[PDB]
Amino acid sequence: MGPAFEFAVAMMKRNSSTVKTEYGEFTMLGIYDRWAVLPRHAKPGPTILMNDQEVGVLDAKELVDKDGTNLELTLLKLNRNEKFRDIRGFLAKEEVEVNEAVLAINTSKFPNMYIPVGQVTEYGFLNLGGTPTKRMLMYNFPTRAGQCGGVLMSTGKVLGIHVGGNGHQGFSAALLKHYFN
Amino acid sequence: MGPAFEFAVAMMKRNSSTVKTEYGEFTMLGIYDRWAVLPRHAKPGPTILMNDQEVGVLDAKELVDKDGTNLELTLLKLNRNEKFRDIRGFLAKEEVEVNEAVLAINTSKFPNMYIPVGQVTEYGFLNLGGTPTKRMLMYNFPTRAGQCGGVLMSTGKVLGIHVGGNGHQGFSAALLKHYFN
Ligand SMILES: *[C@@H](CC(=O)OCC)[C@H](C[C@@H]1CCNC1=O)NC(=O)[C@H](Cc1ccccc1)NC(=O)[C@H](COC(C)(C)C)NC(=O)OCc1ccccc1
Ligand SMILES: *[C@@H](CC(=O)OCC)[C@H](C[C@@H]1CCNC1=O)NC(=O)[C@H](Cc1ccccc1)NC(=O)[C@H](COC(C)(C)C)NC(=O)OCc1ccccc1
Image 1 (cartoon, protein in one colour):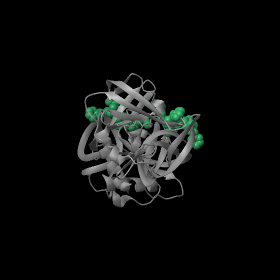
Image 2: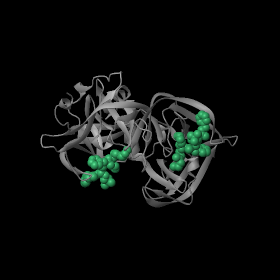
Image 3: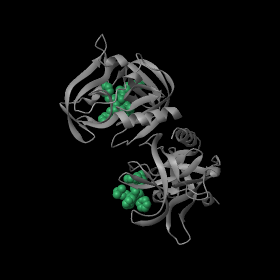
Image 4: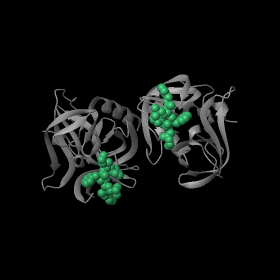
């Protein structure tokens, strides 16, 4: 939990930004090069507001699996010269389970706030907002609107991105190494 | 920062609650016996909602110093049989400065969220919402409405209660040992 939070904070400082799409305000983790990730329901258009500045979106990939099932992630390539710090070494090849994770959020509504979510379990299939969705990671903590995009982390690992929630159960889309390339 | 967050979380689990007064929703640290603390501007009436339940307020002390200057703390004695875990050993005799503090919040709006605020400096006098106020602790982080009552902590220490903020500067009222008794 403690080394989780230390990792979480250093990672948010180096690789996250606050983004606005027409569909709301999100935390955004940049991954490597000009590629970042948002929840799919962030629905990025041709331009987004990153740290209050218009940034053109050169490409958005809505991620689905081999059967077209929603993974609730949108990869985006940014029209910007600054490259993100390569963090793909922190993404696992498959869905991570951990005893101690922190969820990290960084928006106008939740400015640099961290939640100790505890154990993260590979939940897998979840019908989320009426959309059958896979590779879900689940954690218990009281979820809230505005926390999507939050970055789920433990010591040495970026597990995924917060995309949904009901009640006191939160859900991240696993953020997997091979999504990058 | 890491051992700060571990301490913060264990302390919030053992001694904090979510409170509603007519003036809003607050984090509330219980200190010992039936005595807890709220920001003064929480303005507790004869009854409050603690963890969604009506609790009678048997006594509220608005704290001022020897010259009547606002300290922005209200001590309250709760009409309840459960005694708080005695935490006065975690309160200092004078205002604490630290290199690494976490601010801990626990309301419907910010449910179990933690902010790494960094260095806490004894700020002292501050005109806050038009009220000359003393024993202020200052930390840099983007403050928000709804975070009052938040508990400012480092490893082994409860420094104070969040009571105000402007811009990217936050302020706690130092929570001092001798306020208790
Ligand atoms: C993040 C987005 C946001 O706030 O909008 C603009 C900034 C938001 C966070 C959740 C809200 C409350 N708890 C949260 O963590 N994400 C969403 O609202 C999701 C949006 C979405 C994702 C994928 C497809 C379609 C929409 N939607 C949900 O989380 C959705 C909301 O339902 C209620 C009940 C919470 C209002 N949850 C959902 O469909 O859960 C199904 C479920 C989950 C677990 C057990 C049973 C059922
Ligand atoms: C907590 C209470 C709340 O949200 O209400 C019901 C739930 C709230 C938290 C601040 C809001 C934005 N930043 C915060 O951390 N606390 C307050 O609003 C304080 C209430 C109060 C305390 C003591 C006496 C009277 C009222 N008030 C402030 O923090 C006040 C708000 O001013 C603005 C500019 C932020 C809107 N701040 C203030 O007066 O600051 C003076 C100052 C501070 C530092 C440098 C220059 C000036």
